[PDB]
Length: 429
Image 1: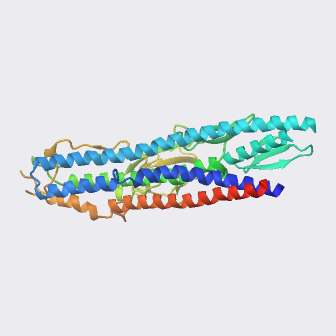
Image 2: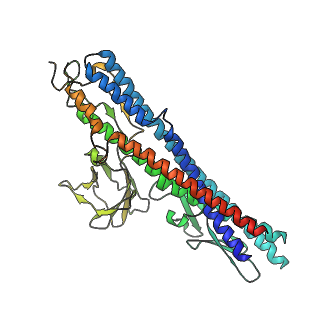
Image 3: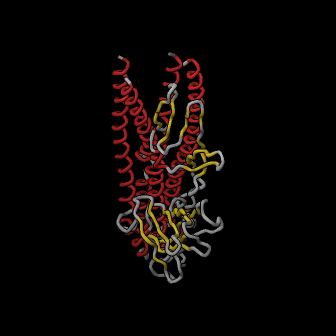
């Protein structure tokens, strides 16, 4: 029977995690499966309108339609990204709610431990039920002391319940990222001690953490990379053309720039890094943990965990996947920084060419010629996203990848939920 309860608890914990991640991932899936919004469609519409234009580069109506489609493309990028941003905010709130529930359960369990210790059937049951509900949120190991009192210990060793004593966790901004809520344990003297997420990868809390870092962040970076690569390559080409009044074409799109967060554990909080894109086709869909080891800068890509020592250019700027990172002065050993090259790409994206006449369809100044227009339409068949995918290939793959990860989690979660029901039955009888 003891073994039975344990196995059941283990399975509920696993199930809570899978189910949470499946649920959150299904939101990303549904957002992307909708063809009535697909960036593939907004992109095709943009390119179709562009092909229409390439045929009669002089037609102001066709020029104006292109602008309309450029606006819709950017608006579709922004709509999708903002939904992902709203989901991130919900994850952060859910983390806080999880911590509050955990704290609550822990105090309840400690008080029950106390009541029980004084009598020493229903209190034993009430405690067991509370323990199982807590273990659904975050994994805890039960141990019992003489007198029959329960200890509840987390994977990192934090004693959430020590007989009559309950301890608490706290939802706090992560040290690496001020916009990110994470979890800490509470030391009486030192305050909040952050727990690395890898140690909270159990239960619904672990499902939220895993979804955010492995699914949500990556979706946002892949979408961001696409918008960036598209914006920069279209702009680069547009500016080599000449508009209807014979003037040099200008940047057609605005795009958000890289952002870098200085770890709050750093020696001097005023030390910052900045990053700028210098080759959009080498920009990756990842963030970067960059650590100054006293001599060199060690970089770890969040997307694939690959690492490397950064080389510096003549100016002493770090050279990272199509970016240059300015470090300045003040860096101490073990100082850490989180570079996000594309996460704000979309929120600051906009159409700069408002005037139908300002579209640069010509290769030569009129001072008809649709050569540059054809160069822009050819971008559709070019591998400018990460150096190896076209715009269409990059979105399609994201859609596909999310869809597949979703279906798989659906299977795992249904299976695990069934395991829970089967074990519970075998327990009741």
